[PDB]
Image 1 (cartoon, rainbow, N blue to C red):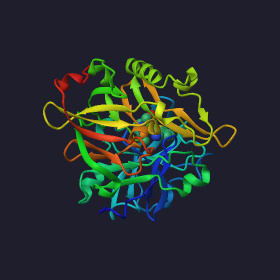
Image 2 (cartoon, rainbow, N blue to C red):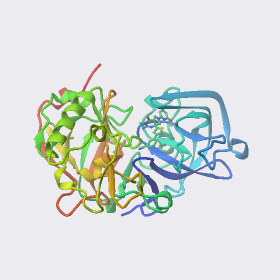
Image 3 (cartoon, rainbow, N blue to C red):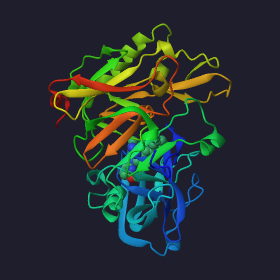
Image 4 (cartoon, protein in one colour):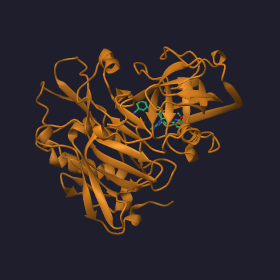
Length: 390
Ligand SMILES: COc1cccc(N2C[C@H]3C(=O)N(C)C(=N)N[C@@]3(c3cc(-c4cccc(C#N)c4)cs3)C2)n1
């Protein structure tokens, strides 16, 4: 590992998101910030809020600059509103540089800040095209690259614990690494396989085949990317298009049919529990997503285990049982490879070469019989047809 200063700089879990420490203003104001490859704004709480124990105080920063413009961001299941400006921003456990970046000072929000969550803002790492209010507001990473010599690439190792982490534990535990400007070889095993970034807005990719325990879901591959497929550290679950979700759940139920689970479990609403240590991992299937490779007619696959798609949750009776929620759910906005997918791999966002790399994560949860995997190559024809166009 050549980036020791950035290794283990993340904290959190899939259900609450993973965050990194950042500072804003002069003198520096420290804040915990959610790492989000699913958005492109750097936005931080800038006013008192019941669920925040600290926030950005613009009046105390000598380097604060008011852009005299507001921003309103309503998203499904939540929203935030704020005031735009710029200031000096740094990442203590990151590159040793300070950059002037845009900051959306959140003055009002709805279902944005979660009680128990330890972050006070979000770092949108995707492209300008989806920045709010529009693409003229340069994203943080673009500013970083333009103002310093930091390579146009970052990589993420999100580490799920495999069991519940209480309030004390989640604050005292290492949740992963965000390597800014490079690839740390200590974070993965095996080889890195790259899939092209289809278009630079979200980190869009193309899935060309899906298997449940080796059995081909056998759907027109266009269905897998309808209306798009993205890699999003800011989404907890692996989300699949309605029709794909229906087919996948049917296959996962069939593979695990030796035990019957309630509809609420499959809907991701209710937890299921087993006596301590007896979770029947082996009855659940592995899931393989084949992604377009960099070479013509070549693909590779990433395989996850139920240890990735069954999210550990504390039992309501805080018993000694091991409980989980099914972390695969349906979407009407395309496939979203969220945290439970990313927890199995070291993911390289190679913006410079317009590609995303995947390798087995050194911190993925597994058992003595199965492990997550990244394998290739496979001959796959007409992969462009798998991409959707409106
Ligand atoms: C910040 O600026 C902007 C701009 C436009 C949109 C935008 N966002 C759209 C939201 C969204 O719907 N997704 C999917 C996402 N990728 N990021 C957002 C949030 C995620 C969480 C959150 C909470 C808990 C856990 C996890 C996890 N894992 C994530 C809260 S808001 C921020 N942000």
